[PDB]
Amino acid sequence: DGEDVQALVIDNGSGMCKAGFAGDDAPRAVFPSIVGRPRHTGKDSYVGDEAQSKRGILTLKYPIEHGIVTNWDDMEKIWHHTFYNELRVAPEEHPVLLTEAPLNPKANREKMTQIMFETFNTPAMYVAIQAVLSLYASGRTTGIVMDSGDGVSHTVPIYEGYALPHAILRLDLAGRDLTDYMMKILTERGYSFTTTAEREIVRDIKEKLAYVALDFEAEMKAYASSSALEKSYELPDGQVITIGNERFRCPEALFQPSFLGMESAGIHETTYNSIMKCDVDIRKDLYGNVVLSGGTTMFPGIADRMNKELTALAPSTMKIKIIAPPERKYSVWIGGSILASLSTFQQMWISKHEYDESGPSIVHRKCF
Amino acid sequence: MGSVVEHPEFLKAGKEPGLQIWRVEKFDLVPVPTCLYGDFFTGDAYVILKTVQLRNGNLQYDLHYWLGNECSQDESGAAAIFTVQLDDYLNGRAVQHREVQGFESATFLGYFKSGLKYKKGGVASGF
Ligand SMILES: Nc1ncnc2c1ncn2[C@@H]1O[C@H](COP(=O)(O)OP(=O)(O)OP(=O)(O)O)[C@@H](O)[C@H]1O
Ligand SMILES: [Ca+2]
Ligand SMILES: [Ca+2]
Ligand SMILES: [Ca+2]
């Protein structure tokens, strides 16, 4: 796709990579962030859906864990696949915006930068924090983003365009944990979901039928008495199963991590704690601009439940607003697309010239 | 190495006490004709800088990004980012404010002595 120079936007997540062209309202390519290599022989590699389909003969790996790159050789294959197989571009002809997680280690930031300039010969590149881009996509400069994906959740207070690092909180409770939990409770129901292919079916049941109950205890009851809210789901073979309270117990684990044997605070309490770590004078503006982002925030009912819970934790006169855009699976990416399209961003990128002069540590000064 | 905005409009911003208004137009920040100040298209987003003279010789800045009910996501996103960029350009000294149609602060509404007015329509999305 491509005004004058066409910038690219790539949002790399633990579970999914979202990539596309700056100026588009949505990522053109969305694929699983999985690299597969032969269990025996041909060097060779597969990415995304093709790796998944050849899983019996490949060793599959996820280069990103909890939002952070832990394998750079496999990350390079994601990126190569992104440029040549998905976007069909020559990376040397385009400025590239990449995203990162809140608090990404310093060395990781340098490596991404080095890889783009030395492996892919990008003419220019930039690295942005994912939560800050979602805040921008919602048309705000101040607020708190609760970003939840497949591997990590974060609460990220932002003020006048910038994250407040001391107040950011990380919770290793996210989509993958919920899929796994749904496998466990559907099993207890009487079914059997334990295998890899089964995990894929369950991931789809969670995405299609799960929801967050506004009142968890009154819901268990409505279900314990009546059958009216149970749902049918058709398996790939035509068998039809019935889902009952597993529908809301699954995402309930976001608010009650003990359901997963976890000692942590839930997403509502993590959001509160992040707010309370900020200066008292900006907290009203945080409560008033709670932005949800990421695929694990797409459960129906989640925004109403966050509103109820934060209302209970804050003073009764505090105005609370939870913003949950219908496009929030891709808010990160869209924010990056807007940022990279601005007439005034020309000046922001790291150019190849700047890289050649200062090396990878240039990122600490240009990308903040 | 720096990241200094070179957009002609940043060079004009906040040079003297007064009101300055720009409209987001296809991912660019465009000056509004001064005879049209106070009439906002509800399908658009704008950035407003109010500069007040301080006893001190230096200038006080309040940046307000105004969001029409029908403005597109690229327009509200861009108005917010241009606000951050202008504030940064001004050495952080501006106080930023988000202004939503129908819910603007009294201070913002007070900038328009003949009363702000909404009109339907606007520039098309830059997406
Ligand atoms: N409609 C849905 N309802 C519930 N969960 C969903 C829905 N759609 C997607 N998800 C889940 O969202 C997760 C992927 O979201 P996302 O792309 O934001 O994550 P990521 O960026 O890959 O991960 P992370 O941000 O943790 O590194 C998966 O767990 C997926 O099952
Ligand atoms: Ca993500
Ligand atoms: Ca418009
Ligand atoms: Ca400021």
Image: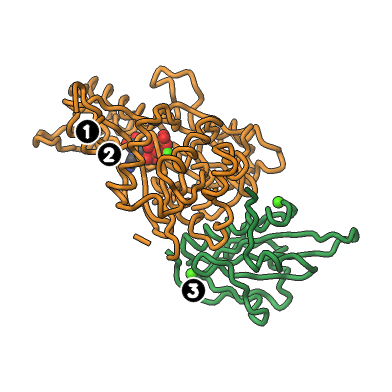
Number of the front mark, 2 or 1: 1
Rendered image coloring scheme? by chain
Among the two numbered marks 2 and 1 on one chain, the one whose residue lies closer to the N terminus: 1
Chain A pictured colour = orange
Residue at horizontal 54 percent and vertical 45 percent from the top: A132
Viewer-side residue, A123 vs A256: A123
Marking on residue B123: 3
Residue that label 1 marks: A52
Examine the rendered structure and indicate whether residue B124 appears above or below residue A24.
below
Dividing the picture into quadrants, the one containing residue B52 is: bottom right
Left or right, residue A335 beside residue A13: right
Number of the front mark, 1 or 3: 1
On whether ligand 3 comes within 8 Å of the CB at mark 3, the answer is yes
On whether ligand 1 comes within 8 Å of the CB at mark 2, the answer is no
Residue at horizontal 81 percent and vertical 61 percent from the top: B59
Marking on residue A209: 2
- For the residue marked with disc 1, what is the amino acid? Gln
Marking on residue A212: none
Name the residue at the right extreme: B55
Q: How far apart, in angstroms, are the residues tagged by discs 1 and 3?
A: 45 Å
